[PDB]
Image: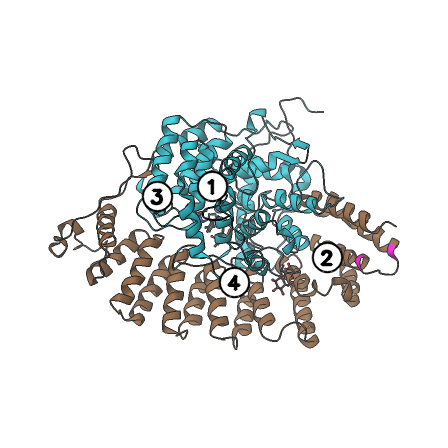
Amino acid sequence: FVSLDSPSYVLYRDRAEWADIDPVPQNDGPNPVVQIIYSDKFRDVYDYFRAVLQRDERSERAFKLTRDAIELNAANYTVWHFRRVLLKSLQKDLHEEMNYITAIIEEQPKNYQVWHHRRVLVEWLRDPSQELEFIADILNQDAKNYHAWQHRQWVIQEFKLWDNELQYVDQLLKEDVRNNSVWNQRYFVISNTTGYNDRAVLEREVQYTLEMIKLVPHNESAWNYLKGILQDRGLSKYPNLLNQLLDLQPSHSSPYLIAFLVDIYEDMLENQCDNKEDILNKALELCEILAKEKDTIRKEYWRYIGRSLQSKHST
Amino acid sequence: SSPVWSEPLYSLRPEHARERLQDDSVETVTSIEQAKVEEKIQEVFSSYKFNHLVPRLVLQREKHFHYLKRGLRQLTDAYECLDASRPWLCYWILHSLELLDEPIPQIVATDVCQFLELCQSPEGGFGGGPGQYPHLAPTYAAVNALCIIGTEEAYDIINREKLLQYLYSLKQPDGSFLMHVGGEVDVRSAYCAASVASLTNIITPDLFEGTAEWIARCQNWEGGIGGVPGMEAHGGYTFCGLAALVILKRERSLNLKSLLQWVTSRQMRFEGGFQGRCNKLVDGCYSFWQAGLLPLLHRALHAQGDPALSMSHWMFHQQALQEYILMCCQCPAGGLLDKPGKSRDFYHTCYCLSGLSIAQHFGSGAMLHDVVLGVPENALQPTHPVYNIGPDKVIQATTYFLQKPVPGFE
Ligand SMILES: N#Cc1ccc(Cn2cncc2CN2CCN(c3cccc(Cl)c3)C(=O)C2)cc1
Ligand SMILES: CC(C)=CCC/C(C)=C/CC/C(C)=C/COP(=O)(O)OP(=O)(O)O
Ligand SMILES: OC[C@H]1O[C@@](CO)(O[C@H]2O[C@H](CO)[C@@H](O)[C@H](O)[C@H]2O)[C@@H](O)[C@@H]1O
Ligand SMILES: [Zn+2]
């Protein structure tokens, strides 16, 4: 009907159709703390929301009122909950409500309540047909919106919409290879579909990641994904990887590469590698280089790694 | 060494310039934003250096105190967006005043207690304001605020019987908790529940059944913890996850090695502060959410008898974090913030100060080692890494409530 900013908007205390119900002012106590000096419009809407909530009035007027309360404070979870109670009682058209939540999220995508409301609607309708496209639009505006990605994972997993997600991940990585949210989605997609136990899949992933690292050597996300897909089996289980990284070292001694080498050495020592003393010396030299020169912000961590290595493998 | 009036800074060393972003000549939105922030931060760093003269950094206590004191009573309509988070405003402000060692007048303490009583729901828990449904976030905030006040008047406001029933009403069979009735679930709920339950002594054997395992499922390939299983690691959710596990004495459920490497990697080599997730920007509030994980990891590893743990420092750059907060996160008018260019708010004031305190104080067993950068008056009161309220407040509250029985349970 009329929005809060509409020229013809009328305060609830002035609406004839609301005259039969008394507004309920907020009880802040005689000596209030953290007292918000509300605008007249804000207080007016909330005084009436408090009244309908208190009377548990499941009406169309109460339903429209929640829309105004939400515009005033979309983080008010009590209003959202009551709105859902009304959606059910009044048997409101859920597709119409989906259109509403779509507009709301577009305006305020960084809010927990709006995304939760949308999830409830999709669950109620058992209809995910608009989800991937809607989410892609939000991500088109902020490619790292946490709520958007979380909602995306839920929809895909709940309705088994895995088919085109790796392509979506690939497109977004092409747009910004440093987008950590996308590398996370890549892991989410693969672990839930083919898994990483398939050696052909793992090889494809290791090659792809190494390629990305060569393109942008200082992009930490690619380095983290490489370790992430190999860490559970153990970094020392991939002998060729060590050699490849070693060749790259002179021309690409980034703290990421050096740190990865220490991680490999750590695992080697943990697995009764041959040349223990040699590997330990190499690992300690690298920890020193990282602590003193290449990654000084993490000097306390690297010094701790050096002491751990000695407590576990000095013999 | 140096005269007492000049104190060399890590961020001002000539080698520090080497820490600027290397974009490999491949620009993307991420590198462009990072470079913009680094450019601004360098300007700020340079303004604190006068060739070989580097005056001691100063925490503007009095200005922060006046901003906080004013906020505790009244707020502009710019705060209408936090009308469903009023107990948070109480907690953020009280905790900041507590860190600054500014006493709470009895009148103010009583008024806060009365207000929080009005926010408490008859079904248990606290809502965002009077008459609002209860929600775990403001419940966590209200309980912490009451514990900061620490009077019997404050402790007694909590309806423990209903609080426990309320927690049960949110508990899911997979071990997770809803944030509120008909609400969303994420790691924040588990921490909010574990925090209030342990402080008020209402933990039953079944309350947290499966919770430790659900939290472990949230730890991802990165080593950090996401909001729910499968999601990207974030400092906010990682703090919640690890702190909850520490309360439950189930830290070992996590791969502490990958968590440790992940959190330490979140400290920005150039800025000195912490980012919330990989490839995102530095932000003063992460001084708490991220850096706070180090005292938790230390405690955890120490419990396992790790012989390589330091006996004097947390495993992050304590000095650099203090430099970032003191030089880049203070609003000249009082209050602290995300990064230069942003406006002050109570949330950032709370967390920037909480992080500053963690960076200043190391304690493990009988070992205590302080690193207070700048003038000596910068030293803040210590904060408990699990609850983020004074350790004295934690002991006093737990001692008080341990004298009461777990509601309807033996
Ligand atoms: N929750 C949360 C949350 C979400 C996003 C962020 C990301 N973030 C980092 N710096 C500023 C922010 C954005 N925050 C400010 C605090 N806040 C909030 C409101 C009520 C209570 C609490 Cl603790 C926090 C929010 O909802 C949004 C931080 C925290
Ligand atoms: C007890 C309790 C309520 C704890 C809350 C902890 C916390 C800070 C959670 C963060 C959640 C989140 C969605 C961050 C992303 O916001 P963003 O994209 O705006 O920030 P970013 O760029 O720094 O990731
Ligand atoms: O940080 C990796 C570490 O986390 C655990 C959970 O504690 O598993 C996470 O990471 C795996 C990838 O390494 C994922 O397969 C798993 O789903 C995720 O929970 C540990 O098993 C692992 O060592
Ligand atoms: Zn912040």
Pointer 4 indicates a residue of which chain?
A: B
Q: Position of residue B89 (x, y in %)?
A: 40, 40
Circle 4 packing at 10 Å, graded few (<14), some (14-19), many (20+), is few
Colour displayed for chain A in the image of the structure: brown
Q: Which residue is mark 2?
A: A260
Q: Which residue is mark 3?
A: B119
* Between discs 3 and 1, the one toward the N terminus: 3
Q: Which residue is mark 1?
A: B348
On the rendered structure, is B37 left or right of A103? right
Q: Residue at x 46, y 42 (%)?
A: B341
Q: Which chain is cyan?
A: B
Does dot 4 land on a helix, a strand or a loop?
A: loop
- Does the beta carbon of the residue at mark 4 sit less than 8 Å from ligand 3? no
The stretch of residues the image draws in magenta is A270-276
- Does the beta carbon of the residue at mark 1 sit less than 8 Å from ligand 4? yes
Q: CA distance from mark 1 to mark 2?
A: 34 Å
Q: Which residue is mark 4?
A: B174
Does dot 1 land on a helix, a strand or a loop?
A: helix
Q: How many marks?
A: 4
User: Residues at badges 1 and 2 in contact (C-beta under 8 Å)?
Assistant: no
Circle 1 packing at 10 Å, graded few (<14), some (14-19), many (20+), is many
User: Residues at badges 1 and 4 in contact (C-beta under 8 Å)?
Assistant: no
Q: How is the image coloured?
A: by chain
Does dot 2 land on a helix, a strand or a loop?
A: helix
